[PDB]
Image: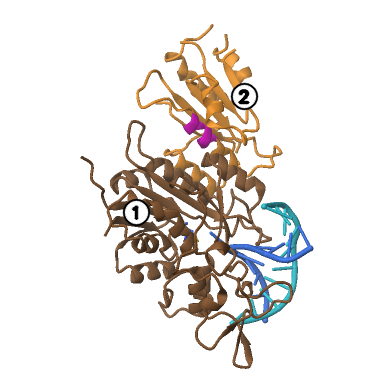
Chain colours: A orange, B brown, C cyan, D blue
Amino acid sequence: QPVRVLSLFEDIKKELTSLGFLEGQLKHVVDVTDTVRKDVEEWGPFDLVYGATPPLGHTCDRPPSWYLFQFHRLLQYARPKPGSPRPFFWMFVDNLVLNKEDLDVASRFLEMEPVTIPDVQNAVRVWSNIPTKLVKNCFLPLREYFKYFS
Amino acid sequence: AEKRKPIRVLSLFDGIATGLLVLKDLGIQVDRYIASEVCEDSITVGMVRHQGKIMYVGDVRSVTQKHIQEWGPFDLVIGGSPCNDLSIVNPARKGLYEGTGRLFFEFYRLLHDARPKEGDDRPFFWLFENVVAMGVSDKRDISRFLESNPVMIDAKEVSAAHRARYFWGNLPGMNRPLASTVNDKLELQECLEHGRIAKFSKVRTITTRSNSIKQGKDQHFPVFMNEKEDILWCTEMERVFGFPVHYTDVSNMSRLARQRLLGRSWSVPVIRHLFAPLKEYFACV
DNA sequence: AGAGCGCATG
DNA sequence: CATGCGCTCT
Ligand SMILES: Nc1ncnc2c1ncn2[C@@H]1O[C@H](CSCC[C@H](N)C(=O)O)[C@@H](O)[C@H]1O
């Protein structure tokens, strides 16, 4: 099946084409404060939903936890049915901007301990349902379940 | 033929167990009452006043999905998260996302774990309470997470104090008009002990701060007694909130301690007003 | 224990 | 404009 993706707080469309997921099927929102459940359902059922905190040293009005909570919210909005029609995965990425308390909250909410991925102190954390380059390897495995347009 | 069963309650941020108190007053038979509290004074009050009926759990953020599944299904889920980082009465508030504010999401979270799975047609009721004096951003965000708009209820209409509060939830008839009862004490005078004269008919919102008892600009003493002005006694304050007399007289607590408990508390007639239609949904004792 | 600060907000 | 599920600091 083709691509169906929901991107939050960051756009991986440029990366989605690079790893071979583009063909219009991607949706991107910056401010999700006024986004309801219907707004998520009406954009068609998504197979994968992505969201990530801005790189630290970037400018953000929002607290580190805001991204997490909004992500979890829209995530619960995006999940399908008790019956499982197709494969559904999710991914949240921390750019080392999350406090110990906040990343503990993240692990509590997403019911999963983060996988930490190093660059080679320029590393990133990730929570994902999966069974830049180094984590691009994490963007990779989706090709087995979803057709690639190479 | 489905019969009515005793009610199963999960109470987050339980305080001095206003929920169980009201439920029992309404004659609603309580199967189990599981409370999440961390303040030892409050937990003591709940433990003593309801004789070990309350099953206590630790921090709310130590409660997991497996716990909800294991602690049976819940008919009712009620909670009021701390508002010291939400209320505009606190200049140094850290907002909904930092400090104690984020605890709201802990309610949110747990609610969805307790919500009966799709294809489950059992009755599920939930109630979330917080203050009106909060920032518009935080209020909107809370409304977005709970996917609902709050209902403002003011205890002024049914008690001897101002208590404008937002209530999110799905209890039947949340928007219905409040109705005074013969048991209700609407004037401060009705709350006082013998030989005491009330300067006021209603008092302003009672916080945990001692001088929230003081009225208006000039910080007037609320009562006058035998050639000497005075503030509210803890018993009088209990009466104002609608609690039974000497409810918080436990654990050798000072005035400030009791008031710290009550200032964070619920207005009993308000919660009774909200839980009132539930006595028709569950077994009566 | 009690007084001051704080200012967005309905 | 009067007001507040509080903190701080004696
Ligand atoms: N992390 C936490 N986990 C569980 N309870 C907490 C908590 N942090 C604070 N609390 C409790 O949550 C309460 C919120 S005040 C609400 C009290 C209650 N609704 C009543 O009617 O009295 C406080 O009393 C506080 O003791």
Residue B279: mark: 1
**Chain for numbered disc 2:** A
**Chain for numbered disc 1:** B
Q: Is residue A76 magenta?
A: yes
Q: Please state the horizontal and vertical placement of residue A42, each as a whole percent of the image.
A: 54, 22
Q: Please state the horizontal and vertical placement of residue A25, each as a whole percent of the image.
A: 57, 15
Mark in front: 1 vs 2: 1
Q: What residue type is disc 2 on?
A: His
Magenta segment main secondary structure: helix
Question: Tag 1's secondary structure?
Answer: helix
Q: Quadrant of the C terminus of chain A?
A: top right
| Label 2 packing within 10 angstroms: few (<14), some (14-19), many (20+) | some
With respect to residue A120, does B90 lie above or below?
below
Q: Is mark 1 within 8 Å of ligand 1?
A: no
Q: Are marks 1 and 2 on the same chain?
A: no
Question: Tag 2's secondary structure?
Answer: strand
Find out whether the residues at labels 1 and 2 contact each other: C-beta distance under 8 Å.
Answer: no
Residue in the picture at 53% in, 28% down: A38
Q: Residue furthest top?
A: A150
Q: CA distance from mark 1 to mark 2?
A: 47 Å
| Label 1 packing within 10 angstroms: few (<14), some (14-19), many (20+) | some
Q: Which stretch did the figure color magenta?
A: A71-77
With respect to residue A113, does B41 lie above or below?
below
Q: Is residue A59 magenta?
A: no
Residue B193: mark: none
Q: What residue type is disc 1 on?
A: Lys
Find disc 2 in the rendering and name its residue.
Answer: A28
